[PDB]
Image 1 (cartoon, rainbow, N blue to C red):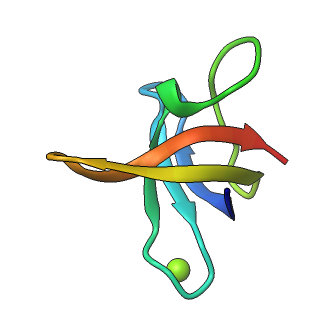
Image 2: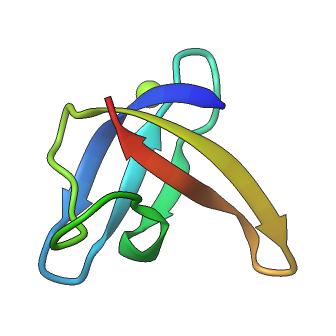
Length: 66
Ligand SMILES: [Mg+2]
């Protein structure tokens, strides 16, 4: 599991980016967010996650707030 923080997140639509030091930002969709409740993220939130890549390119998976 990779570590980063939320660069920004559009809570209305439910997407944004995780920034990772020395690496490309990673797109994150609300559907990747683990845990209970309304799936959202705040700018600056630490997260652990994986990067999953299919034909659409890499995005975050298994995102847990840290
Ligand atoms: Mg950067």
